[PDB]
Every structure is written in C-alpha cells, then in structure tokens.
C-alpha cells in the first residue's frame, strides 16, 4: 500500500523485491550482496537455494560473491540458462545491478514452464 507502482524508474524494481521478502532498498546497487534473490528463490522454489548459507549481513565484497555463488547454484540446480556476473554485482557500481535485476525480474515472472 501507499506509494504505488507504475512510474518513477529505479524504485520500480526495488518495489518488486521490497514487495517479496519485505525489504526497503532505496537503490539498485543495494543488491550488491546477493541475498534478496536467494530469499526470493526459496519463496518461489523451496529447496533451490541454501538460505541456510547465504550471508544476509555481508559487509565485505568477497562475501557478496559467495552470496551469489549460492544463488547461482539456484539456477544450475533448477535449469536457468543464466550465468550470473557476480563480479559485476559485487562491483557496487550500479547498472551492472540494474541491467541484471531487470532481467532476473522479467524471467522470475516468466521462467520455466509451470511453477
């Protein structure tokens, strides 16, 4: 509720996640960790990721990678022909996160047949 969802780019995606696991990201770079996705996955596909491994409090970069490393496994596990960059998501330079999240979202909506 409130705010809405339609215009105002950037926040467009944030809302997605925000309205998925109950987040509050202000920027895209905020996804320079690799947790949201994980959580999102578990929510979609139970037993696809290792929520009991992901670092939902990673402050260092090296960490981020790992976080993604796991998430990435969520794809090679199910069957997602997508090789997450990570190295780009752990760059915290934006764009590489937006140009990635946008996809993830798109796919997430319409990924594998059924499910």
Image (cartoon, helix red, strand yellow):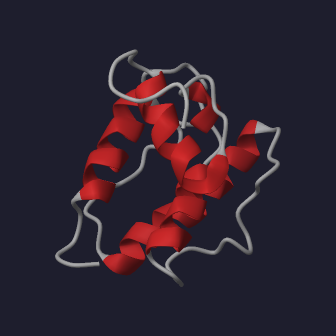
> Front-most of 26 and 54?
26
Residue drawn at the location 53% of the way across and 27% of the way down: 28
Give the image location of residue 86, x and y in percent: 52, 44
Image x and y of residue 112, in percent: 22, 71
- Name which residue lies at 76% across and 54% down: 56
Q: Position of residue 48 (x, y in %)?
A: 49, 78
Quarter the C terminus occupies: bottom left
In the picture as drawn, the residue positioned furthest to the top comes out as 8
Given residues 12 and 33, the one toward you in this image is 12
Extreme residue toward the bottom, this view = 47
Q: Residue at x 35, y 78 (%)?
A: 78
Residue at x 76% of width, y 57% of height = 55
Q: Visible in this render: residue 88?
A: no
Image position of 65 (left or right of 76) = right
Above or below, 56 relative to 101: below
| Name of the residue lying farthest toward the left | 113
Is residue 89 visible to us here? Answer: yes
Q: Residue furthest front?
A: 2
Q: How many marks?
A: 0
- Residue 40 in the image: above or below residue 103: below
For the residue pair 25 and 49, the one nearer the viewer reads as 25
Write down the quadrant of residue 42 in the picture.
bottom right
Q: Is residue 63 above or below residue 32?
A: below
- Where in the figure is residue 26, as x and y percent of width and height? 62, 24
Measured along the vertical axis of the image, is residue 33 above or below residue 6? Answer: below
Q: Nearer the viewer, residue 8 or 42?
A: 8
- Image quadrant holding the N terminus, namely top right
């Amino acid at each position: 509720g409130s705010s809405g969802s339609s215009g105002q780019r950037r926040h467009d995606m944030l809302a997605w996640i925000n309205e998925s696991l109950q987040l509050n990201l202000t920027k895209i770079e905020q996804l320079c960790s690799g947790a949201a996705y994980c959580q999102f996955m578990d929510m979609l596909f139970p037993g696809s990721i290792a929520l009991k491994k992901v670092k939902f409090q990673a402050k260092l970069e090296h960490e981020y990678i790992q976080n993604f490393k796991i998430l990435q496994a969520g794809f090679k596990r199910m069957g997602v022909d997508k090789i997450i960059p990570v190295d780009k998501l752990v760059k915290g330079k934006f764009q590489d996160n937006f140009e990635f999240v946008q996809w993830f979202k798109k796919f997430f909506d319409s990924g594998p047949s059924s499910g």
